Length: 127
Length: 272
Ligand SMILES: *[C@@H]1O[C@H](CO)[C@@H](O[C@@H]2O[C@H](CO)[C@@H](O[C@@H]3O[C@H](CO[C@H]4O[C@H](CO)[C@@H](O)[C@H](O)[C@@H]4O)[C@@H](O)[C@H](O[C@H]4O[C@H](CO)[C@@H](O)[C@H](O)[C@@H]4O)[C@@H]3O)[C@H](O)[C@H]2NC(C)=O)[C@H](O)[C@H]1NC(C)=O
Ligand SMILES: *[C@@H]1O[C@H](CO)[C@@H](O[C@@H]2O[C@H](CO)[C@@H](O[C@@H]3O[C@H](CO[C@H]4O[C@H](CO)[C@@H](O)[C@H](O)[C@@H]4O)[C@@H](O)[C@H](O[C@H]4O[C@H](CO)[C@@H](O)[C@H](O)[C@@H]4O)[C@@H]3O)[C@H](O)[C@H]2NC(C)=O)[C@H](O)[C@H]1NC(C)=O
Ligand SMILES: *[C@@H]1O[C@H](CO)[C@@H](O[C@@H]2O[C@H](CO)[C@@H](O)[C@H](O)[C@H]2NC(C)=O)[C@H](O)[C@H]1NC(C)=O
Ligand SMILES: *[C@@H]1O[C@H](CO)[C@@H](O)[C@H](O)[C@H]1NC(C)=O
Image (cartoon, rainbow over the protein chains, first blue to last red):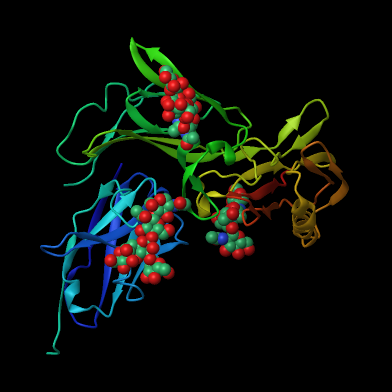
């Protein structure tokens, strides 16, 4: 039993940075593996990043390789997503997910409990 | 559509009979989470028509890689476990028996099983999660009345620092034994029969006691037994009322394919 809630989302310019946060409650945080997902309006839900139980193994996708880095803090019962060099097509609602069993899958099958999702929209063409 | 989580459980048994035969609108998965404690045994009962990937074809947790390993037997990580996969007709209906026998000395493990009904639509799933792990990590000096000695056993039991494939996190690999220092009495530290126990833990415990000069101690023997490398130390008459705790770290000791040790933490109480 675990619930999730995202924060830190909003509006940003191209090449900026956002510190997305996701807190949990209920069952022990350090006993579940966390991972971020996003769904662009119209397109389907794709895999973003993933962090293991202790935080040693990180699993990322090709679209956000290097740009997005996932970090977890077992003490704070919170997982973070550091987004850097946001390309304009990153405009999507970013979902937080927790998985009781996790074998490193890059899909939504292993994740059981999900959050709500915050809106992240990035503009471009200077100002 | 979120993946709906259902939960079922019985008395030391996981019954999925006549619970996976319907079709929901969204993806669902019924869970049976169990944590054996006092050497209890577990039964997994489900309909024979369901496709069950359990026991010999389970998903086991690997502490070395901090992930799960697919399609593996659980005896490959907890050898003392033994099971049987038979065909019984429970409550009239043909059922599948997944009876596991959990000994007391069986090493800690963490694996899951997938109970999937064969259908063109895979919206419904069954899962059983098994979490065998020690839950007591803080005990006292077990004074053996026969030999008149104190024992802090880290070679087995709850304070076992032997490399195990149990689901323990970074700040959970902390076991501790508390020995209220009785002057001029023998104190035993039973440790696993390992090569590096004498090579690094024995120098580690020596340096912990020599730094404090007011601690009166005398190392007698390092006796190799059947399975325990017992450190025999006698603490003499102490002067100042002090308190000491020493750390014998084996959590970093890797053991193929997934087993990892624990950090021993012996707390010495010097009270008059
Ligand atoms: C237990 O079982 C599960 C399920 O099979 C396994 O989980 C899989 O784990 C593997 C890795 O171990 C995952 O493989 C990864 O798949 C990614 C999917 O990307 C696809 O889509 C993009 C976009 O179209 C394509 O470009 C891409 O080619 C794929 O078609 C790959 O992107 C990953 O590639 C990575 O490595 C290559 C080589 O270095 C790099 O070039 C890439 O940039 C990237 O870094 C990778 O191949 C797989 O997705 C997981 N799920 C599934 C369903 O297979 C567990 O691993 C398994 N565990 C054990 C212990 O057996
Ligand atoms: C984990 O362990 C379990 C068992 O503990 C494995 O599950 C299966 O266990 C059975 C044990 O009997 C394996 O044997 C299979 O038996 C099937 C039953 O058919 C027999 O009985 C009927 C009458 O009831 C006869 O008419 C029939 O001829 C058989 O005598 C067979 O259908 C199976 O497949 C093939 O067997 C022979 C040999 O080639 C062929 O002649 C058959 O026509 C048929 O094609 C088999 O004999 C069974 O193999 C086990 N399953 C699998 C997939 O192998 C789990 O598999 C195991 N998990 C693993 C290994 O990951
Ligand atoms: C068990 O937890 C303790 C802390 O509660 C860890 O103690 C470490 O002790 C060394 C001794 O010099 C310190 O330098 C470290 O800073 C301590 N760690 C922390 C996180 O404070 C000990 O390592 C733990 N045992 C493990 C993880 O096996
Ligand atoms: C050892 O156990 C004692 C028990 O009081 C505790 O105070 C101490 O922090 C522990 N040390 C380590 C390294 O875990």
